[PDB]
Image (cartoon, coloured by chain):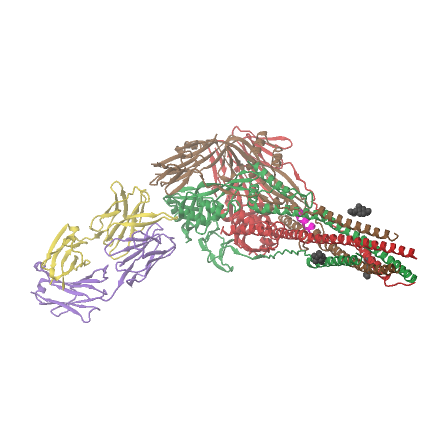
Chain colours: A yellow, B purple, C green, D red, E brown
Amino acid sequence: QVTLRESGPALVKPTQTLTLTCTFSGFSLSTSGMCVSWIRQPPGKALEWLARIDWDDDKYYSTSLKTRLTISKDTSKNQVVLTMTNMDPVDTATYYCARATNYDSSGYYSLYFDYWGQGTLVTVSSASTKGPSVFPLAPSGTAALGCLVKDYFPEPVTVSWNSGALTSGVHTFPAVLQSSGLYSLSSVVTVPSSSLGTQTYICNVNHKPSNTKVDKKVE
Amino acid sequence: DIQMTQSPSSLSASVGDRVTITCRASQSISSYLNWYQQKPGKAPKLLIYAASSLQSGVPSRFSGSGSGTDFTLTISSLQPEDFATYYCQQSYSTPYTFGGGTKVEIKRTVAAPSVFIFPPSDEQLKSGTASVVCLLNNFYPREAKVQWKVDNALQSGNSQESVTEQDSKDSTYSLSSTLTLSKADYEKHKVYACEVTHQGLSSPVTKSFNRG
Amino acid sequence: NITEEFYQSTCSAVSKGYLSALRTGWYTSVITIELSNIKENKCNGTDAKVKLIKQELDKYKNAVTELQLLMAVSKVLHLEGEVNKIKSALLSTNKAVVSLSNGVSVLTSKVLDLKNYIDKQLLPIVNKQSCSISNIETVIEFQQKNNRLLEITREFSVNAGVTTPVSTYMLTNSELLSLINDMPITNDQKKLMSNNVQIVRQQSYSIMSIIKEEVLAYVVQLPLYGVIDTPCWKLHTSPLCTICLTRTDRGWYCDNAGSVSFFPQAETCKVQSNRVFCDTMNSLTLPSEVNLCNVDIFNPKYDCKIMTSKTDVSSSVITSLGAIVSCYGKTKCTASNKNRGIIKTFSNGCDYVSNKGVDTVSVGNTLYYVNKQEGKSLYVKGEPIINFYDPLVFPSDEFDASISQVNEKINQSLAFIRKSDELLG
Amino acid sequence: NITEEFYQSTCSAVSKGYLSALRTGWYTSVITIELSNIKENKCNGTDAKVKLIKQELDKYKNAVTELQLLMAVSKVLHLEGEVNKIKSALLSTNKAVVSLSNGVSVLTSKVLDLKNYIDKQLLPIVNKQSCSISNIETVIEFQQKNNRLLEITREFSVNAGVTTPVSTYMLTNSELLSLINDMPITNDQKKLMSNNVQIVRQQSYSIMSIIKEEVLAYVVQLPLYGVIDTPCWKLHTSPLCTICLTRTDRGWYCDNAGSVSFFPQAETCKVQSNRVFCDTMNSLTLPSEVNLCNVDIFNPKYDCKIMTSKTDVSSSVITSLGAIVSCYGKTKCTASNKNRGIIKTFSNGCDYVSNKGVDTVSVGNTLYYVNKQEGKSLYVKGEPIINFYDPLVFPSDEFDASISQVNEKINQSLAFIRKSDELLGLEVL
Amino acid sequence: NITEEFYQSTCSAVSKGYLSALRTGWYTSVITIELSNIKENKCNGTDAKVKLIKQELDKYKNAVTELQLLMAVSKVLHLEGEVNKIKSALLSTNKAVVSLSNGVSVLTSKVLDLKNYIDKQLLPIVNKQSCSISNIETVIEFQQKNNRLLEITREFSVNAGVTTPVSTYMLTNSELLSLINDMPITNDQKKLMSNNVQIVRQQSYSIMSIIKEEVLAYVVQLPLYGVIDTPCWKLHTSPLCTTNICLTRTDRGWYCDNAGSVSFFPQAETCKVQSNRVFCDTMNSLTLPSEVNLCNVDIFNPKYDCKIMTSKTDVSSSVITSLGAIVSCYGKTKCTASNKNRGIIKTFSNGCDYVSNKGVDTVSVGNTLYYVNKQEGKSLYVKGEPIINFYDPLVFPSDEFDASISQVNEKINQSLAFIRKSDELLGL
Ligand SMILES: *[C@@H]1O[C@H](CO)[C@@H](O)[C@H](O)[C@H]1NC(C)=O
Ligand SMILES: *[C@@H]1O[C@H](CO)[C@@H](O)[C@H](O)[C@H]1NC(C)=O
Ligand SMILES: *[C@@H]1O[C@H](CO)[C@@H](O)[C@H](O)[C@H]1NC(C)=O
C-alpha cells in the first residue's frame, strides 16, 4: 500500500510559523521519478498547489507564496516537511500532502498526484483552545436520537456511535460557528423505536486539539 | 501563471444522465492535464491523468478527452455516488494550477423531510443555557424553510442551521436548526414549536413540545 | 489514432500514437531453385547458321559464370473389199492405242515428277520449318518456365550478388508468409509482419550463396523484431527566438524496455499507417526524462541538446500532420490554402499550422508545401492484339468424285473388250 | 562560374558560384496504363503440350498477383488365211487395251494416293505450323506492345512497389515535361526542371497504387522547389595545429530567405554544372554569420562548430577544384604531378593545392588522388545480323506443257477411232 | 584472426584484427559497345500486319531516344458371217479405246488440278511461313547477340543514366581484371582488388556518356585505394552507470590507421566488410590522433577528451556486436541471457556485462529481446522439370510409290508390244 499522513498543529497563532510533517510508506524518495507535493485548500474553496520536492532534492514553490515556504525531505525517516512563516487567518485551510509520479510513455512527462494524504486542518486564530460540551438529544415507527457537541475551538470534532458499530442512519452535521466565536454541531441517528429500551446508544466525541474524549449515553 | 477555467461551476443531473464537464487552459498545454474527484470531507482522488488516461480503480464510466487548450471530463451514466466536486489540473508549467471546480449534485424525486424536535437536556440547563434542536431528515430538494415559534411567536437571530452534504445512496439532504436561548428566557415559555415548510409537504409540518 | 501536439515553449511538434517494431535480430532461410533445362534437339532447321537453343544456353551459362566469379465370183470379190476395208479400219484403231499409250506415258512420268517434287523439294523444307518452330518454342518455354530463376540472376548481376529489398522474384508472397510463420516469434508478430509484407521486404536482404548451371541457391535475410506495440513518436523542431535556439534531437523515438530509444537517422525507420519499424543497430538509449525537453529547454532533469545563434533566423519545418513556422525579424511569413487564398499572416514568433487548414506556407520568398500537390492525370491507351490463322483446305470430296468417275470409265472400257472378245471366241 | 577559396586561417576551402534549388514540396501525378491484351486462338499447333499464348499470359497474371499481395479356190483359201490373221490381229489389239487399262487403273489409284497424302498427311502439318507461327508472333508482339507496362511491373516487383529514381519506362520525357508545365511553380522553375530532367528524376519517386490484370496505375511523385537561384557553396575542412582544431560543419550551404540552409548529409544534394538541388527535409537553419567562420574560428558573432585534439594530426581532404593538405608532426607530405613526379614538399602547417598543377598528394604512406586517373579504353564489337529466306518455286509452265501434250495425244487418239469407224460404214468398188 | 575485447571500464567492445583499404581516388575507363543490327528482310510473311523485325528496332530506337534526352459356196457364206462378227467386235474395241481415252482425260485434268493446288495454294503459304520463321529467328537472335547492350540500356533507363554497383553486364570479370592490372597502384593492391571484385564493384559507378542508335558508350568509375593493410577495428558502446549518473561513449563506428593518425568512419554505409577485410571511404571521414584509443580503457584520460553523453537517471539496453553482445542492466530492469538449448542460462545484476555468441543465442533486457546470433530458418526449394521439344519428321513412301509407277510403265510397254504384234500380222 502507498499511504500518506499529515501531522501538525490544529491551531496556530497569527504571525507564528506553521510546520507540517508528511509521513509516507509504500514508496521511497530514494527512488527516481518519485515526488511529494503540498496542496492546501481554503474552506469551501479551490485547491492550491504550494510546494514540491523530488528524489534529487529539487524544490519548487508557489510563486506568490514562495518567500514564506520551505520544503525539505528526510528519506531515512520517510518524511517531507513544509514550513510556512507568518501565518494569517486567511491561511486557514486543509493541508494535503500527495505523491506525484510522472507519466513516462509516448514522449510525455506529465506529473500527477496518484495518492493523497487524508489531510490535516490547520486553523489560524488568536482565540484559545476549548474542549466541547456534550449533551444528549433524547428520543420519543422509527424515532430519532442524537447528541449535541456544543462550544469548542478549533475544528475539527469527530462523532461516532457505539464505538463505530452503528453506522447506518447516522448523520453528523457540519460545525456552525456560534455568535460566541465557538463551534457547535449535532450528530443524530435514526433507529427503530422498539429498540429504545433494549439497545444502548452512546455517542463518542473526539476533540483532538484539546485532547478531549467523551462518551455519552442517550435514553 | 497558467489559468484553468472549468465550466460549468454548478451542475444538476438525474441518475443515468451523461454529464459533460469542460476545462480550458490560458495557453496550450498539450496533454499535460489531470482530472480529480473530491467527495465531501475526503481528499481529492485521481480520475484521469494525461488528459485521457484512466487511472486503475476508477469505474469505466469516467473518461477524459482533449489536447491543447480545451479538455473534457465525461460520465456516461451518472450515479448516486458520483456526487463530488471535480477538479482539472495542469502539469505543464512550474506552478501547478487547478481549476475553479465543478460541483455536481444529483437530481432525484421529491422526498418529504421527517421532522423531529428535541428539548434541551437537564444537563445543559444546569449551566444556564438551553438549546432547542429540530431535525429534518432525508429530504429533497435541499431548499427548505424552518421557523421557530416560542409560544406562537416567530423568533429571529437566535437560531442557526446546517445542512448535510447529499447522500451517496438515496441522494437526500438533512438539516438541523438549533434554537439557542438562555435558561432564564427558556423557562418563561411553555410551548416550543419547530415549523417546517418544504415542497414535499402539502401543508407545513409543525413539531412541538411543552416544557415539563 | 495519430495526432500531433505542438509545444510553443520549445518550438517543436510531436507526432504521437504510433506502434513500434524494433529490429534486433536476423532470420535467415536458404532458398534453392532448379533449372528447367533444355535438351537441344539436333536437326536441320531453316537457317543452318541459326542455333537458337544453343545460343540461348550460352547466354545463360555465361551469366552463371559471371556470378560464379564474384565469389459366184461376184460375192468373193465383194468379200475381199470387205476384208481390205476392215483391215484399214483396224490399222487406225492400232494407231489410236499407241497415241493413248504415249499420252499415258507422258502423264505417268508427270505424276512421278509431281511426287518427286513433294518428296525431294517440298517435304524437306516443311521438316526444316518444323525444326525451327520446335527450336523457337523451346527457347520461349525456357524463358517462361525459368522466368523466376532468370529474374534472380539479373538482380544478382546488377547488384553484385546482394540485393535489397527482397523482390517478389527472390521470395514470393506465399513463401514469405511461410517463412514468417516459422520465425521464433509470438503470434502477434507473425500477424503484424504477415500484414506488412512490403515493409518486411524493405528491411530484408538477399545474398547470393551458390550458383551452378542447373541450380541456384541464395540466403534470404529477414528482420526479427525484439519488441512490438510500444508507443513511438516523431519529433520535429524549428528555431525559437526572443538570441535563438533550436533543439537538435529530431527524429523517431520509441519506448524500449523502461527507457527511450532514439533513432537519429531518418532512413532507419519505416512507416506504414500507425505502424513504425525501426532498426536498433545504431540507436541511442535515453532516460524517460528527455521528454521534458519537449516542454522546457532548461529542464533541470536532462540537459537538452540545442543549437544557438546570436542573430535572428527564420525557416519552416514540415511535419507529418502539418508544419511549424518560425517567423522572426523583418521576414514576412504567410499561410495559404489549397486554393492559394491567403488565410494567415505571421508576426514575430513560433507558430504551428495544421495540414487540414493550410496547404502552403511562405517564409520570405521561399515557398513550403505542407501537402502533396495533386497534379495532372496521365493515361496510356492499349489495344487488343489479334492473331489471324487462316487454315489451308483441300476439296477432297470433289476430287474423289472425279477419280471414281475415271475408274467407271476404265471399267466400261474393260466391258467393251469383254464384248469384243465374246464376238471372237 | 565555379571557383574555390582556401582559408589558411581556418584550414578550410569554400566552393563559390553555385545556384540553388531547395525541395520543399511534392507534386503527384497519377499515371495509368492499359494492357494490350492477347486473345488465345484455339487451334492445334505443332506441339499440343506447348501452349505458348497461355503460358505467356499465366506468367503475366502471376507477376500481377504478386504485386497485388504487397498491398477359183486359190482366192478363197488365201481369203481365209487373211481373215484368220486379222482376227488374231484384233485379239492382240484387245490384249493391248486391257494392258493399258490396268496401267491407267494403277496410275489412277496412285494419283488418288498422292492427293490423300497431300490432304491427310501434309496439309495438317502445314496448318499446325501456321498455328504455332501465329501463336509465337502473338507472344513476341505481346512483349513488344506492352514493353513499357512490362518494364514497370519488373521495377515494382524488384523494389517492392516503390522505386527511385523514376525510370524512363515509368515516365517518358514528353510526359515529364508535360507534368512540369502543370506544376504550381514559376516559369523560371518550370524552365529549370525542364533542363535538368536527369536530376529531377533522381529526386523523384514512383509509388505503385492500383494493379489489375488489364490495367496498372501508380502515383509518380516529383519534387517541387520552393526557391531557386540563391547563392550556394560547399565547405571542406581539414585539421589545423600550432593542440589541434577541425571544423565539423562540412557540407553544402544555400541562402534560404534571409538565412542560410545547411545540408549535412551528402546524399541530399545533387550537382550538375553550377547547379545544386538540395532537400530541406533534414536541414539546419543558420544565420548568415556562419560565413565568418571561414575567416575566424573564434568569430564573436557565431560560435563555430569545431572538434579539438591535444595531439598532433595529419591527413588530406580532396575538394572540388583541388585539395587541402594538413601536414603536422614528424610526418612528410608532398604533392606530385603525373609528368614531373614530386613537385612540392609540405612543411608543418595547412596548405592548399590546385587540381590544375597537382595530380596526387601523399600524406605519410597514404596517397590521395586530386584528379580522376584516366584509364584503359574498352570496346565490344558487333556484327550485322542476317536473315536467310530462300523461297520455293515450282516449274509451273513446263508442267502445263507436258499436260497439254497429254491432251494432244488423247485428242488425236479419238481422231484415229473416229477415223476407223468411218472405214466401216462404207464399201463399194 | 578476428577477435573482440570488452572494456568494462567504459562499457564498450572493440573488434580487432581487420585490414584496411581506404578509397582516396577514382579510376575512369571509357567502355564502348556496338550494336549487332538487324536488316529487315522484305518479303510477304504470314500476317501482313505483323512486322516483328520493325516493331523490335522501333522499341530499341525509342529506348535509345529516351536516354539521349537525359543529356465351194459353203465356205464363202461362212467366211461372210466371219467378216461380219469381227466388224462388230472392232466396233466394241473402238468404244473401249474411247472410254479409256475419256478416263485418261479426266485423270489428266485432276493431275493438273493437283499440281495447281501445290503451286497456287500450298507453295505460297509455305514460303510465307519461311518468311515469318526467318523474321522470328532474327528477332530472337537480336535479343541474344545484344544481350549486354540491352541490359545496359535498361540499367541506364531504370536509374536515369547512373548506376551502382557496376553490374556484370556493364563490366565483365575479365574486363574488370584487365582494368585493375592497368591502375597506377602497387601489386598488392591489384591483388587485393582482384580478390574482392564484389566489394570493388559495389564501390564503383557507371555513368552513361554517349548513346547513339548503333553504338553505346559510358564511363566506368572504379575506386582507387590510397593505402591498404593497416589495422582497423570497430567500436561498439553501451550505457554505463554507477551503483547516480550514466554515461555513453558516442564515437561508435569503424577506425582505421591512416598515416600515423586514426581515420574515423561514423557512418555505417561508408565501410564495406568481407571476412577480415574492410573497405572504407575517406570522403567524409574524421581524422583523430592515436590517443583516442586510450578512451577504450580510460574515460578521464588527460591526453584526449573522450566524447560521451551523460544521463542523470539509470538506463538499460543491449548492443549487439560482431562477436557477441554488450548488456547494460541497471535499475529495477531485469536482463537475462538465454540459449537455444538451455533457455535462460544467466541473469544479469546491476552493471555492464559482455556475452559471447559462442555460448549465448539471445539476450533479454526488460521486455525487449535481442538476438546475439542469426536465427537459422526453414530451407526452401523450388523444383524444376526438363523442357522437351517434340519434332516428328514427315516421311513419304517414295520406294513403294516408285514401284507402282514402274508397274504402270510395264503395263504400257506390253500395250505397245501387243500392238506391234497386231500390226505385224497386218503388214507392219
Ligand atoms: C469397277 O470394277 C470393280 C470390280 O468389279 C467394282 O468393284 C467397282 O464397283 C467398279 N466401279 C468403279 C468405279 O471402280
Ligand atoms: C483437243 O480438242 C478440243 C476440242 O475437242 C480442243 O478444245 C482442245 O484445244 C484440244 N486440246 C489440245 C491439247 O490439243
Ligand atoms: C519399257 O520400254 C522402254 C523403251 O524400250 C524401256 O526404257 C524400259 O526399260 C522398258 N521397261 C519398263 C518397265 O519401263
Q: Position of residue D369 (x, y in %)?
A: 59, 35
Q: Position of residue D28 (x, y in %)?
A: 53, 54
Q: Is residue C222 left or right of residue A190?
A: right
Q: Is residue D57 left or right of residue A88?
A: right
* Along the line of sight, the residue nearer the viewer: E282 or C215: C215
* Along the line of sight, the residue nearer the viewer: E184 or B125: E184
Q: Position of residue A182 (x, y in %)?
A: 16, 57
Within the magenta stretch, is there residue E64?
Answer: no
Q: Which quadrant of the figure shows ligand 1?
A: bottom right
Number of callouts: 0
Q: Is residue C195 visible?
A: yes
Which residues, given as a range, are shown in magenta? E128-138
Q: Position of residue C176 (x, y in %)?
A: 48, 46
Q: Is residue A50 left or right of residue B194?
A: right
- In terms of image quadrants, where is residue B166? bottom left
Residue C173 higher or lower than E308, as above or below: below
* Along the line of sight, the residue nearer the viewer: C397 or D327: C397
Within the magenta stretch, is there residue E132?
Answer: yes
Residue D224 higher or lower than D299, as above or below: below
* Along the line of sight, the residue nearer the viewer: C14 or A151: C14
Q: Is residue D291 left or right of residue A119?
A: right
Residue farthest along the bottom direction in this orientation:
B203
Secondary structure, magenta segment, majority class? helix
